[PDB]
Image: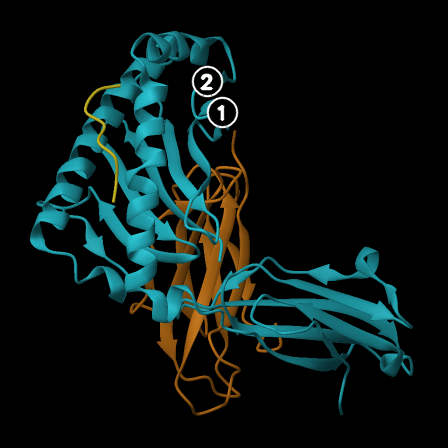
Chain colours: A cyan, B yellow, C orange
Amino acid sequence: GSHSMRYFHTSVSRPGRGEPRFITVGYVDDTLFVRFDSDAASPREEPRAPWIEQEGPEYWDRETQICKAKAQTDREDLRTLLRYYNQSEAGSHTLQNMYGCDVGPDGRLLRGYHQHAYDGKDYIALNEDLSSWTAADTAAQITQRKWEAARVAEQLRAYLEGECVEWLRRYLENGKETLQRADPPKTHVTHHPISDHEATLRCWALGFYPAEITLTWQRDGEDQTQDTELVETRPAGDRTFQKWAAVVVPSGEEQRYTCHVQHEGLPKPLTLRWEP
Amino acid sequence: RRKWRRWXL
Amino acid sequence: IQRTPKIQVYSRHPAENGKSNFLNCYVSGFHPSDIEVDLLKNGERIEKVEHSDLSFSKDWSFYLLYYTEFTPTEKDEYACRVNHVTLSQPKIVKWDRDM
């Protein structure tokens, strides 16, 4: 089906305590597979998924060299940003970047990405054409001119249209047994009295993959999203996710409420109700 | 695998 | 910009008293990334706690999963304590096996 590969990076300056902290992780779909943390004597990128451990030493060597180079460039970039914004070296700042690609079922590129954020806000991002830039403010406009003059877009586009897609296809085949398998959610409805006149109906979805899913509560077939409490999809810690939706109903109306679950791992949408 | 970034903002 | 963290404390599997499980504390939607998270057992800090590597969402806000192996009972009380620059005091969310 449709898949993606994403590399996330975060550098945080640490005034008076040492060099900035640099942490980067790579994901294929919702599966984390590589990590690098600068907080070590001799840090190296490490595997986080079984299907990537088979890569040879040259792979880890190159990845580690790239990670170390990115940490250094980030340190220089943080210094540049302090000048662009006339900020003091005594304050902590954060620089984030994410880049990756999406491939359709045919294995061909669907969309590429490359975007930066400074202090949690959009800084500069590569447009969908993978050839032009969108700057968020005057400071990012300085970077844009520099990147336009240095033909940065064409270099990123070459990587995003080539290696990004080619290596994503490689990982998808090696991890086929898990990355190309959708784990349907295990579902059930729980009942929790709030008083003698009201009760909470909670619809659960557990151990599912990927993370995308839709949970809705209906009363007599009418969507109750306005009165539905929906928690953010959360990780179980075993690579699968969990989510639940709840509604408060007047005691005695419970059997009129049905929970609707939609997940790519389910052949058809599921309808569930409280079964005491 | 990752892309190379040697210099850069 | 600074954003306060959302906090969810839950078990990896439905709680069954006397059976080993994993106690999770998911913190998300926060900025800056400096955060202090602790898992508590009857008000005391648990020491065998691991955590995922810092990552972030589409809106650049960060998220982290803190977890530890535990064996729930009917008497023991569990909680997650989070301190962030956006909180004037640590925030304690008690573990509810029904959430």
Quarter that holds the C terminus of chain C: bottom right
Q: Is residue A90 visible?
A: no
First reached walking from the N terminus: tag 2 or tag 1? 1
The percent coordinates of residue C65 (x first, y second) are 41, 59
At 82% from the left and 55% from the top, the residue drawn is A226
Tell me the number on the disc at residue A132.
2
Give the number of marks. Answer: 2
Tell me the number on the disc at residue A271.
none
Q: Is residue A140 visible?
A: yes
Q: Nearer the viewer, residue C79 or A83?
A: A83
Q: Which residue is mark 1?
A: A127
The percent coordinates of residue A31 (x first, y second) are 39, 59
Is A5 situated above or below A146? below
Find numbered disc 2 in the image and state the secondary structure of the residue it sits on: loop
At 39% from the left and 36% from the top, the residue drawn is A98
Identity, as a three-letter code, of the amino acid under mark 2: Ser
Q: Are marks 2 and 1 in contact (CB under 8 Å)?
A: yes
At 84% from the left and 62% from the top, the residue drawn is A224
Find numbered disc 1 in the image and state the secondary structure of the residue it sits on: loop
Q: Nearer the viewer, residue A7 or A36?
A: A7
Horizontal side of residue A88 vs A58, given as left or right: right
Examine the image and state in which quarter residue A152 appears: top left
Q: Chain of mark 2?
A: A
At 35% from the left and 76% from the top, the residue drawn is C69
Q: Nearer the viewer, residue C57 or B1?
A: B1
Horizontal side of residue A226 vs C74, given as left or right: right
Q: Chain of mark 1?
A: A
